[PDB]
Structure formats: structure tokens, C-alpha cells
Length: 199
Ligand SMILES: Nc1ncnc2c1ncn2[C@@H]1O[C@H](C[C@@H](N)CC[C@H](N)C(=O)O)[C@@H](O)[C@H]1O
Image (tube, rainbow, N blue to C red; front, side, top):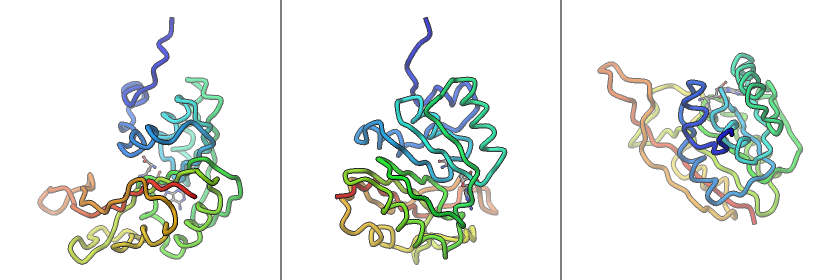
């Protein structure tokens, strides 16, 4: 009989994908299966894990090839509850209500002028009791952006956006990019990480 567990190794070991994001794995201990939106899904590590575990996933990205790859894997695995779209997040408005919206390591790639409108759109489209998970690069006095991302959160800025939500988790811890500097050392930067629940 076919083994039903779909853990953080499943898509990782079968389709050469990076392991499911640590914050997605944590989030699901708290966030129950529901209508989900993965904004900038890439090659789908997070959308695929979610859909395989009962979440109804809208998985969106600008990269047509990345979307094709998600669709390829979706077809192989019969993930009926995973739906894809090639979208430009800089030029996008949406209107469906969701239990869970996540954007993991995507927002720093967007135009700075997109962010206020997108975050407001995210909050608008979360159900009361629903959750938003965001992880994104920052640019701070102690950890300046050395990559030149077109956007990065300032210290305290993500928290300010989500005033009035319950911040189940919020930190601006120093992390590392995978890309390296002139001496081959991983680039150190703070990331804003938040799991927040709407009242
Ligand atoms: N303007 C844009 N609209 C939609 N997606 C974008 C845009 N700019 C960058 N992206 C996507 O952001 C993704 C960033 C990747 N690091 C994948 C993040 C993915 N959420 C993950 O946790 O693996 C890429 O797949 C890009 O195609």
C-alpha cells in the first residue's frame, strides 16, 4: 500500500526541492488546514507540502518555468487541491478570503512602492481568526543591505504593519543568505519573521 505521510523530506527527496521552510513547518502546528494563498511560491516547496497535508492552496509566482514545475509535480502526485497562477505581485489585486496567507523570502524582490498596497490587500483578504506568515530581508543600521534588494523592511516596520493582530511569533533575527560575499562568507542580514493572527 502507498505510504500516506507527507513530511518535510517528501518533495525534497523526490523532486530536488529545498526542504520546506522552517517557519511553514512551525506555522502548521498552530494553523489548521484551510484556504491558503502562497504569494511567490517558487518551485512550490511550501505549496506542495501544504496541499499534500489538506490545505487548499492558490500558488502564485512571476516565473512561468517555476509554475510549470509546480504543475508537473502536481500532476504526478494528483494534488487536486493545489491551483497555480503566473502573476506579477507588483501589478496585482486579489479579492478572495483566506484562512492563511504566506509570503516566505519573496517581498524583498518586489518594488518598494508595491509593499504598502500588497500588505493591506493581504490583511483585507484574511478571515477573522486567519493567519499571515511573512519572512523577508531587512536593511538596518547594524545589518545594512549589501545585496541591493529593491525592497527590505526597516527595523520595526513589519510589526508596525500588523498592529492590532496577535503576533503569535515576531522577530528580526540575524540570518544568512545562501549567496556569499567577496571572501565566500554567507551574507549576514536581519530577517523580519512574523506569524500573526487577525482578530
Ligand atoms: N514581481 C513578482 N511577482 C511574483 N513573484 C515574484 C516576483 N518577483 C519575484 N518573485 C518570486 O519570488 C520567489 C522568491 C524565491 N526565493 C522563492 C520563495 C518561496 N516562497 C520559497 O519559500 O521557497 C521567486 O520564485 C520569484 O519568481
